[PDB]
Image (cartoon, chains in turn purple, yellow, orange):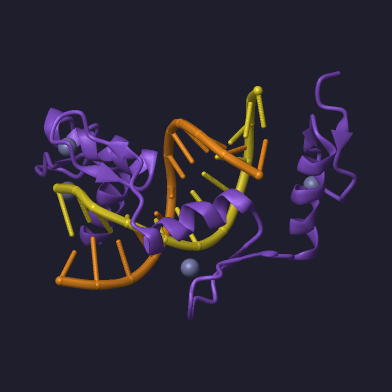
Length: 118
DNA sequence: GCGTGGGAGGGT
DNA sequence: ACCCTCCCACGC
Ligand SMILES: [Zn+2]
Ligand SMILES: [Zn+2]
Ligand SMILES: [Zn+2]
Ligand SMILES: [Zn+2]
């Protein structure tokens, strides 16, 4: 088996291919958030090292993902993904309320719009 | 509308 | 430990 380091916590069946990966994962089961941001006057702490690294981009200003259309840079790949739909004009999320015919590019836009109807 | 955070869960 | 993708939230 390629992932032999198995979590033994109640309710969890996660498994990893390095012991250190299992060790970092298991700390969430006791509520640990050992990855604290060391920027001045920032009390943010995270259970995962990649969560802290993503967070600190708001301090450093590093944006490693660039739009091939307008050359704007973004700190997160998923935010670049939804951004590119502003150029394609794709609106995959349609409101189904009668005589509305509204369409939206992001899923949470439809959620907020659905709550407007009620 | 859409930038851009947090939380989460899958993979490696 | 890093990476990608999704929902959810808040702000203007
Ligand atoms: Zn576990
Ligand atoms: Zn911080
Ligand atoms: Zn763009
Ligand atoms: Zn509608």
